[PDB]
Amino acid sequence: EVQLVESGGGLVKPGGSLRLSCAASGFTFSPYSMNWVRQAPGKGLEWVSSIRSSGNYISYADSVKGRFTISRDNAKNSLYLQMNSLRAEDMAVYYCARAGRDYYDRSGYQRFPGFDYWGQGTLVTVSSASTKGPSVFPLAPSSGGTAALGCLVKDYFPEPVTVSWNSGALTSGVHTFPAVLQSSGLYSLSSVVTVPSSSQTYICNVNHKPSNTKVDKRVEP
Amino acid sequence: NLCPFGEVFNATRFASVYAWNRKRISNCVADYSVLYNSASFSTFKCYGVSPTKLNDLCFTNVYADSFVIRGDEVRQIAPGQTGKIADYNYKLPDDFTGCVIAWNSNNLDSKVGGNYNYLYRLFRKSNLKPFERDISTEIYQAGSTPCNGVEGFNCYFPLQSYGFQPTNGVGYQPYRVVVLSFELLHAPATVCGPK
Amino acid sequence: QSALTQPPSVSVAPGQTARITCGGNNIGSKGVQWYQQKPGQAPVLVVYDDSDRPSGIPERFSGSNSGNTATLTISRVEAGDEADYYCQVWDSSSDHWVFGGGTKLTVLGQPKAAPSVTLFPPSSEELQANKATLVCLISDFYPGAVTVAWKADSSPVKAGVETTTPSKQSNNKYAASSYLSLTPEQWKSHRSYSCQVTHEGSTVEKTVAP
Ligand SMILES: *[C@@H]1O[C@H](CO)[C@@H](O)[C@H](O)[C@H]1NC(C)=O
Image (cartoon, rainbow over all chains, first blue to last red; front, top):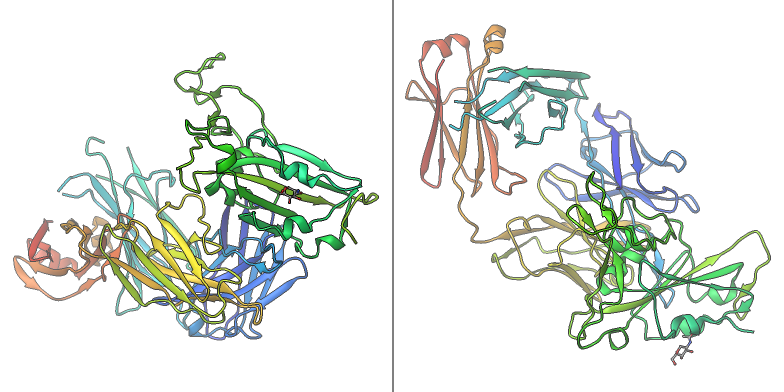
């Protein structure tokens, strides 16, 4: 029904400036107040900002000060966050979320429900390091259920990396294992999918948005 | 003259969710105090307006929508919620300007053997648009094979019965809900408060 | 309201009720909202308006708010129930949404799970590229404590080993990966290279030969 998809993000240099977008489907945008939330790695949730359409009411976190601006296009059903002058503390997964409509109780006190619909999130990475593309290599079928193949994604910074199998319709036990931070600072990921031993060609579609690298490989017996 | 709010609230019989009843309140003066100073209401949520200020505003029309739902489903009546009642029975617009009032009717709408006369819609091809009513009894097609007016495999009756019994829990207990929508058209205002 | 206090952690038996407490002044006036965050996943609203529960959330999840202190109650807890839980309130004074620090639910006495180990040979393609990596994927093990040891020609090798910290999967058992970096000649030099995984004093081994 209702899905909020967040675009943008990637690698930003210290002091660099980054705009983000949140496209919305399934609900009319203006009546609902829309907010931005961030969670730092190994840290708790933090609220960045909120926008309200009625009076263009804008609220920002205390930590964001003159460097972040929140914009909403109700006709486009989209939410924007422009981030300028960025530091390491601003490195986090940023979520766009819809908030329930505030209501007045019988006494007339206003009560605000909270964040019924969230998004998948986008990661902003604040390093002074260059983006490096991944190298997608096949994993020949395993030797032991003998029913699992996979693909290897080597030496990619910064993450995320999205790892697909065939057209993405295949949901037959795909496991995208967590990546490793090597001493080089590059990440390496391995995906494996359980497949019938009796058997169809299988292609792993690897997409790295930060490196502009989209690679699909077919794993062969 | 005076608006017939009591008739909507104190009505002897209430409607099922799929066939929710609409009352048009117009050309009268409305004293909302009886509602907002009352304590018999378990749910009282006003969107886009404060209950205390309502007596001062004037509107072009008021719509009172009446139905009976289980207690756990009352949350769905509020705007922007998913659920069998919200998606298939009664939907409130995202730009809702009005009040939702609900109270327990277990003493009134329950029987020792159980009251199965209150119904809801379990199956529909598409989700309801705001303020849409479906009174259809057509058999639901889950497959390519037509039902031909008979319930069968892959062919189900769209409506289902609430089971209301006195011992059942409060969520499981029947609640009567009235939704007051205050409509402001580009036309002479016919519903006004005491002021 | 500008500050919400939450317990750092709470531990519960598999079948018993769990209560998480969010505390702030006049929290009941505006509303307490609770979120469940599982590792690797976005936050999910479990209760809103101090008591109302979103559709699709099990009836076990319920919330109350008693003045300053608000409690989130899970009537029957499960392995899936474990997550970080956060509480939220709105400030009219500062116009700020306030979040809690978070509470980690840990269900005690959960069944022990054996590690499944899958080892994959170096690519024909990488050996063409002249860089060799052996991948060892460990999945569906509880508890998330594992010791990976790599053996070269049935002799221990500690060179080029890189090991993930255990991470919780959707299937609610931890998962980990190990990578061994070797030169193509070294892969040719020794006939067998393979990964040994020790979980709860049990060593599972998988071997891949060129
Ligand atoms: C409905 O009944 C109550 C109880 O007798 C009464 O006080 C009220 O005036 C009636 N009308 C309403 C609520 O509009």
